[PDB]
Structure formats: C-alpha cells, structure tokens
Amino acid sequence: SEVPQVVSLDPTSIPIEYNTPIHDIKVQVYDIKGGCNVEEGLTIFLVNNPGKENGPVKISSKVNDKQVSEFLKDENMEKFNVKLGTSKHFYMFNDNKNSVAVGYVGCGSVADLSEADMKRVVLSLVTMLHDNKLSKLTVVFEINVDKNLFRFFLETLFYEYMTDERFKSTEYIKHLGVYINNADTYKEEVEKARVYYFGTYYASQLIAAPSNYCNPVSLSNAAVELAQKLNLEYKILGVKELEELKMGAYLSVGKGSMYPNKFIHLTYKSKGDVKKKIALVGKGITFDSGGYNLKAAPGSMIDLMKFDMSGCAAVLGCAYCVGTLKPENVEIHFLSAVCENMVSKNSYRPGDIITASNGKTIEVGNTDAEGRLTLADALVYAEKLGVDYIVDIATLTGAMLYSLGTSYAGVFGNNEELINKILQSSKTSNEPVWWLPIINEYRATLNSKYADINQISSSVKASSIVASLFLKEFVQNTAWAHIDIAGVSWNFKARKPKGFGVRLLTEFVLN
Amino acid sequence: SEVPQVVSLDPTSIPIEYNTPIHDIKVQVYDIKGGCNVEEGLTIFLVNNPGKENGPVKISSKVNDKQVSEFLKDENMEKFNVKLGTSKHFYMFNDNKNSVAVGYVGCGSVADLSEADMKRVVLSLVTMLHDNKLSKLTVVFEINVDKNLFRFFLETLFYEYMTDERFKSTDKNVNMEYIKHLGVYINNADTYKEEVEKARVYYFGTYYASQLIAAPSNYCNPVSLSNAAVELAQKLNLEYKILGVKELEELKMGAYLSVGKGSMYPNKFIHLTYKSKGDVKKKIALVGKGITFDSGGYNLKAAPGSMIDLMKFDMSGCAAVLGCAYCVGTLKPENVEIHFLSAVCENMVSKNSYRPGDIITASNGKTIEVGNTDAEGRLTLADALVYAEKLGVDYIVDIATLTGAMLYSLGTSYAGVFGNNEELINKILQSSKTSNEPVWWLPIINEYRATLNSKYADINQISSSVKASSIVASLFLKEFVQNTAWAHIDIAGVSWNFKARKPKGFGVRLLTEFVLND
Amino acid sequence: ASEVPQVVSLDPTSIPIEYNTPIHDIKVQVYDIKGGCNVEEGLTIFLVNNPGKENGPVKISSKVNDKQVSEFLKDENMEKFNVKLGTSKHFYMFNDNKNSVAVGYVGCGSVADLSEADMKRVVLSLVTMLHDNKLSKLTVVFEINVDKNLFRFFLETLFYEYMTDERFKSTDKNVNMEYIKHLGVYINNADTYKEEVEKARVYYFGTYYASQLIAAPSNYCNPVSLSNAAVELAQKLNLEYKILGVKELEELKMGAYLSVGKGSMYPNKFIHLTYKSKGDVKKKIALVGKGITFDSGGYNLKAAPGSMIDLMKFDMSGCAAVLGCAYCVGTLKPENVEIHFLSAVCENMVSKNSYRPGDIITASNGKTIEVGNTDAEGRLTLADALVYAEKLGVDYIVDIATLTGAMLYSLGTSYAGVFGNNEELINKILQSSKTSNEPVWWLPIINEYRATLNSKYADINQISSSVKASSIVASLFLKEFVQNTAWAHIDIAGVSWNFKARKPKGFGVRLLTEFVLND
Ligand SMILES: [Zn+2]
Ligand SMILES: [Zn+2]
Ligand SMILES: [Zn+2]
Ligand SMILES: [Zn+2]
Ligand SMILES: [Zn+2]
Ligand SMILES: [Zn+2]
C-alpha cells in the first residue's frame, strides 16, 4: 500500500480526475425531419458526395432561418469539397441578429463510413472546438450511420475533446445538439457513450501516467480505489502470497525492481443468477526497460515504455464500464500481474531457468520477452477460478507493427467461438481487431534443451505467433483468446494513448 | 530470344530436366483386402496407435506369406512404438526362402493424420530410401487417409525424393539409385487410383517451379526465363506471346521498364494462354512477380539480414505461374480461359538504373514517386495488373515474394492473401485447403492509404510512416485494378525452405486447384 | 604498349614507377670496429645497449681516433644519457683538425638479442635524425650484437624507411629533401657482414617496388596498367613473360577468375613471369599472388562501418609482393632453379555486368562453385590461378594474398599466417621467415569445417554459412584446387598496410625471395 521512494519528491500516487468537463455536457438529439434551428453556437453539417470523389458540398436539410439558408445555398456551398476530413466554418448574424457559426465536415465519397473515417471526421470537429470559444455545438447528420457508429462518434468526440492536464503546472461547451434521422432510436446510446468515454479516458489516464507516478504499488492502489468507488470486490496479492502460489515467472520479472510485485484481482458479480464466468487478464508492466536485454537498439523506443501496462489499463477501464452499467447474469474477474522490468544486481538474467506456478520450467532467452512470463502465471491463476472465458490483452510483441500496423489489434486463441465473440465485439465497439492463427508447426522451436519449454524462439521471426504458442501452454481446458495491442495502443501521431480495448472488452461482457 | 553474355562462359539457358527419375517410377495401387505380397525391395507399413503418446505397433493387414506373418506377430512388434516419425528395418527369409526387407513408420497416436504430420512421415520414409539401393518400395496404409491426403502423400513423397543435380560436376552423388516401382496397399484401392496421375502432374509442376527458383541468377535471367516459358508453352500447345522492350514502350509500361533500366538483360513480358475447346464460363489472369535477381537497386541490400545472396528466388511468383501452366496445360480443364502473365526483369545497380526520388508513369497514366528502389515488385506488378485488366477477365490473381514483413506476420509456413473481393479470397482460401498449401487472409487497412499521397506524383510507391509493409504494398497494387476482382498472395516468407536450402515450389498446387475447381 | 581504357582523356594510362631512387646512389663502406672509429663529415651515430638494467646509462666502448672526440665521449660525460629503446641525442664539437663534427647515439634497450620489431624502432630513430638535416654522410657504429641476417635487415629497413615516395605530389613537393651520398658502418668482424650490403640494396628495392605498386591508386594501377608494369619489369630483367587475356582465359575455362572481373571496365589480365636458371634445374617453384587492383566488394558492397573500402587499392599486395620477388630473383640470379611468378589480376566492381551473389560458376578444373558473397573474390581468382599453377608441373606452389580481414583478429598487423597441405613446405616458409625477418606464423587447416562448404546445388560453396573463422575456411576452399603438389598459402591481409605511417609495407618480397634461395 505504501509507495516506496528514493527521494522525498518522488510522487506517491497516480493523479486521477474522475469528474471531467465532458460529464457536464447536455446532449439533445433532435429528429432530422422538421428542419434544424440555428439559434446559437456552432452548427456543423456532416455531408458526403457518394461516387463524386472530392465533389462539392451540398446541404439538404432546411434550416429555419432566412440568412443562414442564404449561406447554405447550393450556389454558395459549391466552392467547398467533401474531401474526407476537410472542413470550413463561418461566423455571421442570423435571423435574430445573433452571432452564430455555420460549417461542414467532409465525410468523403463513400457511403458506409469506417471507424477510421469517423475518427478523421471527429478530429476535424474537435479541431474547430479547441480554437472556438463557444457554449453550444450542433451536429447535423446528413450521412448514414448505424447506432453503434453513432455511439462511437459520441465516444470519440468526448475522448478527443478531453485534454489531460494532470501533469501541467506552470472553457468547454455546455450543450451538444445532434440532428439525425430516427432520433428516437439513437437516444438510448448517448449515456452509454458517456460511460464508454470515461472508461476509455480512465485507461488513457493510467497509460499516460509516467512510470515514476504509475508503478506497481500506486497502480494497485488506484485499482483498489476504483473498486471501492464502484463497489466491487478487490483482493491485491503481495510477494508473500505470490511466493506461496509459486508464480516464479511473474516474480522473476520484478526481481530487479524497487516496487514489490502487486497482483490485481477485481471482481464484479451481478446480483442475479450467474450464467457466465469470465476472466480478463491485462499485461501490467509499468515500465519495460527490457532488463539486461536492454532496449538500446535504434528504434526500440525505450522512452515510450511507460505504456507497457496498456492491457491492465484496458481491463480496469472495463471494470469502470462494467461496474457502472452493472450487467446481469455474469461474474467478471479483472486480473493483472503488475510489476516493473529493470536492470539491477537483483534482476533475472538471460539463461535463467524459472518455474511457473503450474510446475513447468521455462528457460529465459530474452529478458524483454517478460510480458509472456507474467501472463503465464496470470493465466494459471485465472484458470483456477473455473471461468468459461479467459481473454487476455497485452502490448506483447512489436512484430504487430509489421503485420497489422497501428490500426488493427491482433487476436489469437484456442477456441473458435471465443475468437468469434471477440470479432463481433470488435464490430459493435468499432475497435478494429483481426484474427491471426496459432500455427502449430512452429511449436517445436520452444523445445528447450534443458528446461521444459523455451521462453522464445531462437530462429522463428513471427514472434506474435510464437508468444501465442507459449501462452497456449498455460491454459489446459478453458476457452482462451489473446489480443496483442502492441501496435495500436499508443497514438504516435497525437502523442497520447488510445485507451484501446475498454469498449471492445465491455461489449464482449455485455453482448 | 538470345541471352546476352559478358564472357563466353556465361550460360545461355536454364537447364531443365523434364523426364525426371520420379517419372520413371511404375506405381500400382493394390486393394489391401486381399493380402500384401512381400516379394522384393523394401515394404513399409504405416502404423499408428490412438491413445498413449507412444503406443506400440500392431500390424493389422493380412500378410500373404507365412514366414513374414510369424515374424510380424504382435509378440514381436510389442517392443516398438509408433512415435510419429519413428521407423525400424526388418530382415527375414520369406516363404520362398528369400531375403526381404520390411519396416514401419510411426504415424503417431492420432486417428486422422494432419498434413504437417503426413510430411513428417514422408521425410522419415525418404530417409529410408536415401542410403539404400532398392528397386521397389511397397507401402501398406494401416491409417485412415482421405483421397486428398493420399495425393498429398504421393505429391510430397515425389518432391522430397527428387534430388536436383543440374549443377553438380565433380560432386555428382554416386550411389544414387532411384526405385523403379512403387506399390501401394490400401483399402478401396480402386478409388485412390484416380490420384496417381494427379499426384504426378502436381508433383512436376511444383518441381518445375522449384527448378526455376533454384536456378542461379546468371543462368536464370529475364531473357532465358522467357525462353524457358516459350518451350513450355510449345510442349503444352499453349498460345504464347513475349513482349519485348519496343512493344512495352508502345504500351507505355513506365513502372515495369524503369525497374530493368539498369539490367544487362532486356525486359521480357511473358503471356501464355490456355483456353478449352468448349464454351468459356470463367476467364482467369494469373500474375507472377518475375524478378530474376533483386539487388535492391540503389537502395542496395546491404543491411544485415537482407539476404541479398538469396534474391535469385525473387521470381518464385513467376515460377509458380509457369508451374501452374504445366498442370493446367497437362490436365486441360473444361470451360476456362487462363492467361499466365509475368513482367520479368532484373533489379541491378548501374549508370542506367532508375534512382530513388525518380518519378515514373505507369501504363494506366498514373505517375509514381519512387521512394525505395527495392520496392520494385509492386512496380512491375502494377503494369502487369493494368495489362491483365485490359484482357477482360473475371479474376486477377497475383503471387509474389513481395514483402519481408511476411516473416513477422505469418512466418515461413503460411502465405498471406489480400484482395478487393470476398468471393475470390474465399475461392483462394478453399483452394488453399484442397491444394494443401496453407494461406491466411490479411486485410487491406484503408486507413493507411493516405500515407501514399505523394506531393508531386499521383501516388507514392511506398509509405514513409507505416511499417505494415505487406498491407501497404497491397494498397498500392489496389490502385491499378479499376473494376475487376483481384487477390494478392504474398509468398516472400514461404517460398524458400530455409532448413532444407531448397525452394518449395509454393503456389503451384494452390493456383491449379483454384483453376480446376471453378 | 597495351592500351589502358579511359573514361575521360585525363584518366592515367600507366603506373609511375621510379627505378633509380636516391638510395641507389649512396656509397656504403663497412669498417671493422677494431682499429678505431674516425669522425669525418656528416653525422656519426653509435648504437649502444646496456644489458641488465633498463634505461641504464650509455657508455661508448669502441675506440675513437680523435683526442677531442675521445674527451667529449668520456664515460663520466656520457652517464647523463640512458639507453631506452629509441632515445637519441645530438652532439657538436671540434676534432683533432679544428673542424666541427656531429655525433650522437641511439638507444637499443637492455635486451641482448634484438628482434626485428626492435630493429625497426632503432632504425626509425635514425631516420628521424636524417630528416630535416642536410647531411652528406651518415656513419653508424655497432656497439651491439647482430647476426648477419639481422644486420641485413637493418640496412634494408634503413633504406626503405629513408625513401620518400613523391610520385603523386605536384605542387607539394618537399623542396628540402636531400639524401646522403655516403654511409659508413663500423662493426666487429666486418669482413663477414660485407657480403650483405649488395643483397640488402637489392632487397630494399624489391620491397620498395611492391610498395610503389600497392600505394599506386586503383585509377593509376588497374589490371591493364599493372600487367603492363610487370611486362616492363620482365623486360628490364630479361625474364620470360606471357600475359593471358580474356580470349585465352575463356579457352582455359577460368570461370571463377573471369566471373570476379565481369563487372570491370578493365579486362582481366593474367601475369606469368618466368625465371629459368641456366644450370641443371633441380627445383621448380610457382609463386601466386592475389591481384585485385580494387575490391569494392561487388554487389556485397563494402558499406559496413570499418569496412575501409577506401583502402581496397591494396587488395593486390600479394601480386606486388610476388613481382617484387621477381625483381630480386631476376637481379640475384639463383643458379639451379626455375621460378614462375603468377597473378590473376582483375577488379571487383558494381555494374549491370557484375556477377551476383548466388551465381554458380565453373572453375577451370570443372568444379562448380556457388557464390555466397561477392566480396570473397580472392579465393575465386586464386582457385583458377592454382589450377593453372599445378599444370606447370612445379615442386612447390606458394600463394600470397590479402585474403581475410579475420587476420586482424588472429595475428594482427605484425605476423602473417601460413597455411598449407605439406609440413616440409610449411617449414621452409617458417625458415625463410627467420632469415628474412618477416614474421610468419603457422595456422591449421581444420578439416572439420570442410562439411560447411557442401553446396546443395554446386560442387562446392565459395564461403561457409556458419563457420566464422574465415581465414581457415578459405584455406579449405583453396586446398580443393591443388590435387598433388606441396602448397602453402600466406594471408597478409593484416600485415600488408602500415596504418601508423599511412603507407604499404611491401610485406612478403623478402620472405618469398629467401624461400627461393633455400636449401
Ligand atoms: Zn518487454
Ligand atoms: Zn514488455
Ligand atoms: Zn525488392
Ligand atoms: Zn523484390
Ligand atoms: Zn574482397
Ligand atoms: Zn578481396
């Protein structure tokens, strides 16, 4: 519980903001039929031009205002194109001689927008908000979007709009109007978007927290504080309990750290009959220097490694969403074997042979492959709960930047139905995931000469699949999936976390 | 048609063995419900024991010789297990008082053997042939096996047994003695017979492709590779055309020709055609990357691990298409028209090579900013795709050793497949299942296209920021298929068998199965 | 003259070669130290040691024939100077004839038997006193013990280090260079060391000649110009010579040697100089030298840090050593021997015409070779050059080559490595090393690595894919191209270039010549 320090100035807790300006935004959804009102604030239309790549802007909806109508006349809206993500907006006086702001965001030439297109649209939207001091924004949907994509649009606008100043030292809007066809069906999605937004923004807060602030001790303390605020059971496992359990793999990674290993175990149990038990496991490495296999090669981005607990952050954000929504007929376990991978006289070293909590011995070939070591014991622990689904999520292998890149997470697993559910949850959360195979032919490269199994392949380069084959050895009789978010977790362009997985994991629990 | 040379000692053609020793093998399939005759040669039993990891071996088939039976009594076979890949040699005097050789290969503890497990059995089998001078091999199938797994057995056996001595001179392996007959004892032998011919045609198509890949770059060049295809087309009675530089100039193939500007061998564009003597219901175009050697260009492969010495394989895609042409041209399917295309060149370093930053114009008008001269595969394939599209086909399928990222995505076992059309990918995925050449579907993330927006040309050859290289190349290729169904098979990672130091001929059976089950 | 191709009219068409060096005009006199040292004009320098104590005091032992110079060199007056190896002091005084003289000393340490390395350092200190001083005579007095072979080494090393190569200086000539015209030497039993004076002079130029060739840059010294250089040398020495061009090389089926050159603008040229003695011929010897006039690496370009591509004008040091040898042999004229000097010269370059990694090529002995790395081009040329050598029917084949950069990690910059298939031949090489004072050290041909040359397609791999001991694996490769003849192979990659002085060593000329005049 007490966070160790080297000097008195070392911080002793993660600053968390629970009450954000987003939560104060009044959101009204009006039916697109009957026309729009432009009586104050910024009014933005979302218009596309199917077929006509880069075609002009044309506004179809009738606005109850003589002056702005004159502005949105086809003859005047012609000079502007629908290039996906392009935008302009103008200030003027309306019928009532009130200064308003009218504009549009180009939604391209495709009709069925993707999550990435939507993201590009929102980015233009937020760009106007951050350089315009208004109190109301109104968005008119002259494009076709389903309920999930609509909810996704709100979540993404909320998340991108929020600016995280916790670590800074030396005026948001208050109303949101949405003009959309079928408003009544879309209304039930607004408050859920608000929950998903924060769940995503909470994970981002932890990830963004640097490793001096966000260490194994303080990160478990935040988990506990989230459980109590949410009224979930919470048990934190310490070194003594961890030795008694024999989690050799997990403890080896921490041997070199000044912060004791802390294993997080949150539990949500719905009030009624329990029909499905689920274990969610997240890689929780608060800083991964690589260990004696130091991240010293050009491109190894050691300065980003505060993010190697992104899986844990996702699983916790899921706890917020799950505890806040309080679904029926489930028991969810949120697990994370937290630690820190450092270079010290005390660290485990390459070549060490260690014994996991299920008795299998493992030969360490590379100390930077530590995430699969910690997940190994977390998966043994999880299977001891007698759950139906074990889903882990982790920034495991940098190889994913060369397979799927920075947009799509990869998912591996030992059960077709579980991989199917994760994909469908990817469709409804709009968090993109792609199914990759656990190629059995590669398993023999983990045949250790001395230990029971190798930690890494010495030859095979498809590390994302090799790790998957290693993890498989630690689940004996339970549907299990594995989601490698190493490439998607961090938004390199915006220089901030994405919060990837929260909504994906929640949709998996909910539907 | 004439291969340029620098010295009179430079080879002017690819050595190609068409009548291989495997071809000289007389295969018969006998019905096991009738006993196995153990006269001469080596006769091998494929046995398993479902249950414990290394159960014991138990011969089930009726052996048509008293002495052998008394020898193969369970009491004698108890000492040996059926560990997958295990084998043992037996010697005895049969009923005729003659010396016979018999043995077994462990088929593991599984009932329905896996493809990868079948291979391991063939290799173990081949090992028994390699240091032995035998005239006949008999194999009794005491394991469950479908027709498709029987053919795959023959197929794999033929390819591994075949030893490529085209380039030996004083190290010709004496003691090499191929068997002359192959006997197969199987249940319902009458139904598996149909697969012997097919396992033969599929075998050679693959070994053919492997001969072109293995052929060093000095032997196998753009001129000599096109010469080889014309001979193949002439044997198979396929229509053939070879576009030379002047025609390629007239067709305005700036991307393709720019790659070869630095080679000493002129560009040669292969176009073979098969069409059957009935109505045509499907018209396919198969495109193969045909880079006979890939130095990288001015973006020289000099970084560690770039394996410049392996780049004679950068035409395995072309080899696969020509290989498919043999199988299709031999079996001759009905109601199809198939164009086998390849834009062959050599990516070299010279005062005549194209440069990074160069801007070139493809045959479809699109200007291209070259960002890395070693991304030359997508350039040649761009002009080949627009060429294929002009033919008015239903399916355009290309197969290429395009991107090294494949090793980090799927590894050395599975090829990746990309496309713009679910239906065609599904047909490739099915064909992958039945040819037994594994492939995994990867997506063309549209979000990355923006990193191809060039500031001066119409399109970027490469992305500057994105590292998912296989996906980006697929996005580039996508810009040269305007309205046709098109899939893309990246074989950069599966083409070369690194452990054996020999090509796999990957793609031949896949492409054929695609053509024949349509 | 055989015409050298050019790109522009300014490209040089010949290697500039100086044959009449200032060292050829110095008159050498050797005096017996018994009977007195006279102190004439110029500089007089004593070589003094003090066995026992390091940095010990210097005492002048020999008898000087001058009262003033004697009084000045009194032991009590010399104790202020030590004998630390290399130290040196200059003295100035008037003699018996009221004339100014200059004397001094150079310290030779406290060890009894100086090594060639120690002699090198003593000579370097002498040269330092010769530079920036307009002297007409230098005299050296040997108050130290050296055998006949080490005394010759002193003269040659003195001559070599004294020489300054200005062939490529135009506006920056040292307008202050003035060489001595006379050199006196005082030593005990002088009559026995006299015979070494003329051999040392011959040995100096032979080595300085190879040095000129090596330092000549690849645009001056290319396959055509260097073969032209050898022709002229054979012509001045009445040596037999035949220069095989591409046409014969194709007839001779030298596919390995030709492949390496396919990418050059200078056609391959094969040098073959012959010295046949007039007497009954008892030994026939073929010396083979690696002749790469510039080694870019080929498509396996030298781009890795520390690859020193800018040094690769020296990949023909073996050929230069062998030609330097030919000068000595042609000049000294051994009596009962037949010597063939061979070099398969070419240039390893990047072009559309170059051979590629992976290429399979056929050597003149019909063996096919899979090219795994184009930067290992030397073993390819030597393979064919060895086949040609055995066809001549000699008693010994000895090749010398800057073959493997591993040499820098095994024996370093001082000792070369000798490999071979024949203990007796390797002993003759080791013997010639002692007498030439050019250090060689025997390294093994480890047969266990042979298997890693087993190509899957060709007859043999050019390179091992797993074994890192390049210098051994190449020896295994070459050994496959000599079937029934004693053959040794001397890798000089590490020792050829003198990094400190920024010039070539000419290493191997004297080693090889001594071998030629061996029992
Ligand atoms: Zn790591
Ligand atoms: Zn990590
Ligand atoms: Zn390339
Ligand atoms: Zn390529
Ligand atoms: Zn070299
Ligand atoms: Zn070299």
Image (cartoon, coloured by chain):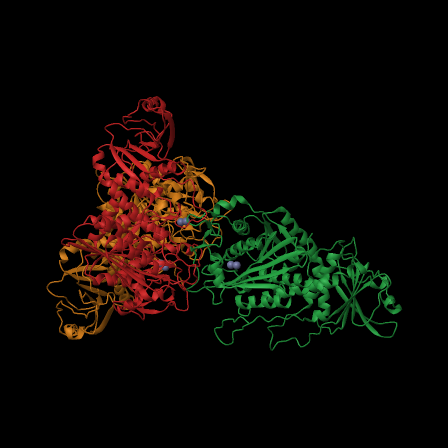
Chain colours: A orange, B red, C green
Q: Is residue A451 left or right of residue C123?
A: left
Place residue A265 in its image quadrant.
top left
- Please state the horizontal and vertical placement of residue C63, each as a whole percent of the image: 86, 63
In what quadrant of the picture does the N terminus of chain B appear?
bottom left
> Quick one: A411 or B14, which is closer to the camera?
B14
**Quarter of the rendered image showing ligand 4:** bottom left
Residue that sits furthest to the left in the current view: A34
> Quick one: A11 or C430, which is closer to the camera?
C430
Q: In the picture shown, does residue A76 fall above or below C316?
A: below
Residue C361 in sight here: yes
- Please state the horizontal and vertical placement of residue B512, each as a whole percent of the image: 24, 49
Place residue A448 in its image quadrant.
top left
- Please state the horizontal and vertical placement of residue B224, each as a whole percent of the image: 34, 58
Residue A321 in sight here: no
Q: In the picture shown, does residue B257 fall above or below B517?
A: below
> Quick one: A3 or A290, which is closer to the camera?
A290
